[PDB]
Image: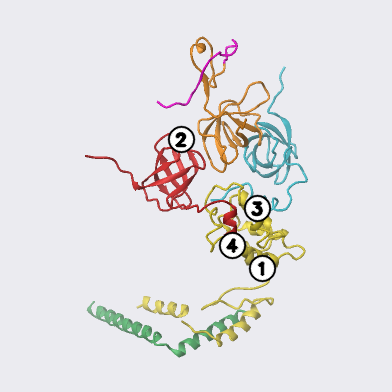
Chain colours: A green, B cyan, C red, D yellow, E orange
Amino acid sequence: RYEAQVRQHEQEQLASTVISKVQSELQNAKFQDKVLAQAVEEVERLFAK
Amino acid sequence: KAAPTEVSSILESKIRVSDEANLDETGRVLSVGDGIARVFGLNNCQAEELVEFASGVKGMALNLEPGQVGIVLFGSDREVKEGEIVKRTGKIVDVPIG
Amino acid sequence: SILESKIRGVSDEANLDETGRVLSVGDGIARVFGLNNCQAEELVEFASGVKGMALNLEPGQVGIVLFGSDREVKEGEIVKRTGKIVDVPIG
Amino acid sequence: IKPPVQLFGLDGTYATALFSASAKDSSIEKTFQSVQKLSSTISKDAKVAQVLSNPALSLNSRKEVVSVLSKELKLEPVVSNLLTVLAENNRLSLFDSIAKQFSVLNDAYNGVVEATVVSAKPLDSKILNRLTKSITNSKYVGPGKTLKASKVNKLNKVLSETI
Amino acid sequence: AGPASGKIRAVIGAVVDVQFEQGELPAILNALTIDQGNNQKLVLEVAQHLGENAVRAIAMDGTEGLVRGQTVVDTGAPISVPVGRGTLGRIINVVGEPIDERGPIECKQRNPIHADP
């Protein structure tokens, strides 16, 4: 029970730090995220046409 | 929240010219079912008057509204449909005696 | 223009802030249309002299319960607001 | 003639009933400019809107007496019959709903919609929406697109719920 | 004379909605006359007002035979009845008419049925 609680606390603490780093990277004006979001919309509409 | 009478079908006839045929002595059945029959028209029809449909079933106009006229059929409503002619006899609900 | 159509209809200003027009009366109820500045449970006054209490404030009209007979109120009567709530004297 | 656009059934049947008689002898282009003048002179004016919420009137300024409210405005053909049906049936309070339903019929049979993301789409008037959406998505992604979203927020919430 | 003439718009049972003009509508508890086919009349008391130049009236007799659009004149006051010493011995009705077949009630005054306590 102590080994499972230590593994669950380490996985929950590591997931909280990775979620905070992903939100801070998107607020720093990512130039690669803006170009990839526009190209994904044109490729999805052409496959269903 | 809205109202009846003029709705979709009855709201597209007053914008052009709703005349030609007389709507006082006769009327068109807009809705019928479960004995009741809502006849659209019959302006000269009095209360509790004998009404005659186009199929042969008799009717009695007991509820008179401003846009429609609720008539109660005295027989079966299987032959009365939407848009049937409902003529007025001119008299009330009478019966024979002697 | 819309400015020339207001003077041809003879409607003056038609301020529905402290006044209102009665649209339906009956069974001790009065559906006064108007009175946007009237508060809840406020005293009112009709054109014939009967008092009212606006308790059902809707969006299109305002339900006021008359304290007298319904024969004095009619369709199209002016209804003024007192500006105060339903109070009584004490001491 | 009933077009496949549904548009409710009770409140939206006001503009659909008058569109059948107005679609003859080419009388649909003049109805678009005449319907916009009736709503712009009863909303942002605060002069002719005195009987918009009151239940009085009763044939005093709505119908019959008009002159400057019909001839001087922009009504001469079938535009005068649309305002007379709303005054007798007490439907003058919702003038914005009748004018908005008339513009949706011309944009469906002679145009397109289906907005993707960000702002609006292109609204082509070709034929099918298969070849029109693929030729307009590549020309609009390069020009403009400030990107100031929906797909990035859904993927981040699924990773935190499985932790 | 300027009589308040009204038009019958609805008739379901004893309730009969009468549509008049704007401003010339009658008040509550007012007798409304209506010409029928016989020598009598159809008394109708105004109960409430639905609006739009229309008020719902309650008929005091048989509503059979009324069509949509008939003339409904207003008396101006309430249901007047014969008072005094002339009403003793006669069979009066709800509208103040004799039902004893003994001629008309020779009354000098006629008070209304609706009055305050």
Task: For marks 3 and 1, give the CA distance.
Answer: 24 Å
Alpha carbon of mark 2 to alpha carbon of mark 4: how far? 39 Å
Q: Which mark is residue D147?
A: none
**Which is in the foreground here, disc 1 or disc 4?**
4
Where is residue A43 drawn, in percent x and y?
57, 84
**Which residue type does callout 3 highlight?**
Thr
Q: Earlier in the sequence, mark 1 or mark 4?
A: 4
Callouts 3 and 1 on one subunit: yes
Q: Which residue is mark 2?
A: C70
Name the residue carrying label 1: D106
Amino acid carrying mark 2 in the image: Asp
Q: Is residue B35 above or below residue D59?
A: above
The earlier-in-sequence mark between 3 and 1 is 3
In the rendered image, is residue C25 in sight?
A: yes
What secondary structure is marked by label 3?
helix
Of callouts 4 and 3, which one flags the residue occurring earlier in the amino acid sequence? 4
